[PDB]
Every structure is written in structure tokens, then in C-alpha cells.
Length: 66
Image (tube, rainbow, N blue to C red; front, side):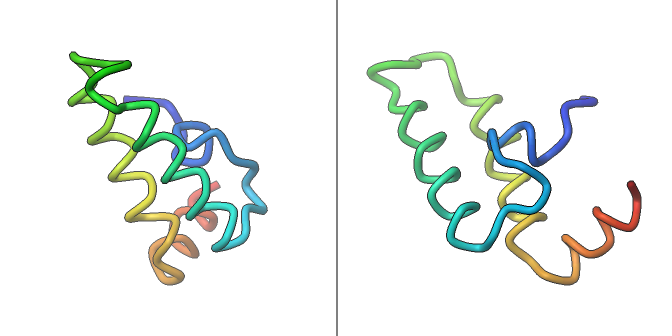
């Protein structure tokens, strides 16, 4: 799945912790099952992107990778 994690959350690569948090909440909610009934897989990708980017060590590895 070659969508980048920043893109998945709809943020720029310079996103602060606050901006990641906001983006994650916005995505999690767009995936309200009342807007997106079949959105389970997409929300796992979103969940995974946030889990990487919100961890300073994992995010450093991710950025180094680029």
C-alpha cells in the first residue's frame, strides 16, 4: 500500500504533534460508520499512519527513509 503516512492523514511532512492529533481525529470521524459503513480497512491504514507519525522514534525512521 504505497500511500505515504502523511498523505493518509492529509497532513504535510512538517506536521506538528497538534496537527497529527487533529488530522487523526478528523479522519477517525469521517469514518463514522454512518458516513462510511464499509470503511474498516481505510481506518486501519489511518490508525497505522498515526501510530508511526505520533511516535518520535518511528517518525524519525520514517523521515530518514525518505
